[PDB]
Length: 285
Ligand SMILES: [Zn+2]
Image 1 (cartoon, helix red, strand yellow):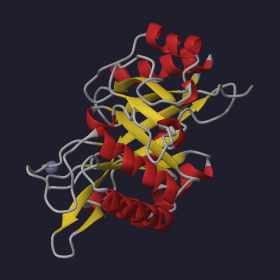
Image 2 (tube, helix red, strand yellow):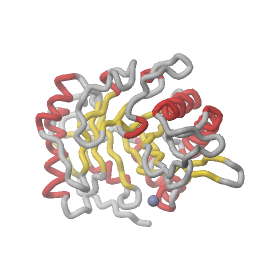
Image 3 (cartoon, helix red, strand yellow):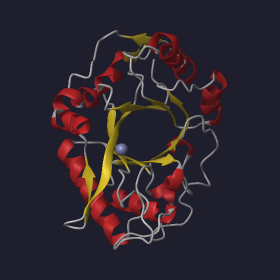
Image 4 (tube, protein in one colour):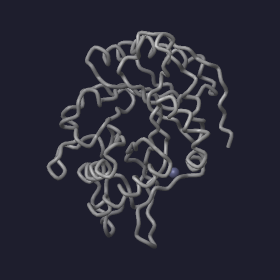
C-alpha cells in the first residue's frame, strides 16, 4: 500500500553507468520506486594555485550529466528521487579534511553555487585520494576529523534545506566535538557505512538519530553483498537506510548477483516484491 520509511541510497559510478537505470526498479504493491536517493559518484575537490582557491572539479562524465540534467537528472527528481553530488579528493594538497575555517566557508559557498546551478539536492563527503602535504600549505591544516566537521557544518549553514551526508570512513567517520557549539546531529543528515558496516552511529555523530544511519552497504561491482539477517536488523533496530554501490543492469553479474540482491532488499526492507522494467539505459556519452 505505502512504502516503508527506510531510504535506499544508490551510488552511480558516472564514469561507467547512466543514472537513469535507477528508474528501472519499482515496488509491486506500493507502486513506488525502490531507490530513494541517487548519489553521483563523483565530483572532486581541487586546488587552483593561481587564485589560491579550492573548487569543485567535475570530470567530463560528471559535467556531461550536469550539463544535460533535464535528460539525466530531472526524470529522477520528477519521481521524487533526491540527487546528491559526491565530493572526493583528487591528488592535490586539498581535501575534505584539511581546510582552515576560512577555506571551509569559501568551499561551502562553492558547493552552494553548484547545487543551485544544477538543482542538486545535496552533497556526500568522501575523504579519499587527496595528496595531503606536510607541513600544511597556507590556509590548510593538518588533516583531521575536526577540520572535516567544520566543512560539513559550514556546508549545512550555506544550504540548510539541502542534504549533507558523510561516509563512515577515514576523517569523516566521527565528529565528536561540537562546531561553534552545535552537535553533529544538527548538520549531518545521513552518515553512510562502508561495505558491511553495521554498528550504531550515535556516539560517532552525537545527536544523529537512528533515521539518519545508513547500514550495511553493498558493493554490486565487487559483489560484496548483505545477508538477509543484516537487512532484517535494519528493520528491527529502526535504522533509516541502506546503500548499494555501482548497480548496473548492463554488467555481466546482473542476473546472477545484482538482481537476487535487489529482490532481497524489496522483500526484507519493504516486505514487497520487485519489478524490473528491462529498459536499456547505456552510457550514451
Ligand atoms: Zn585519480
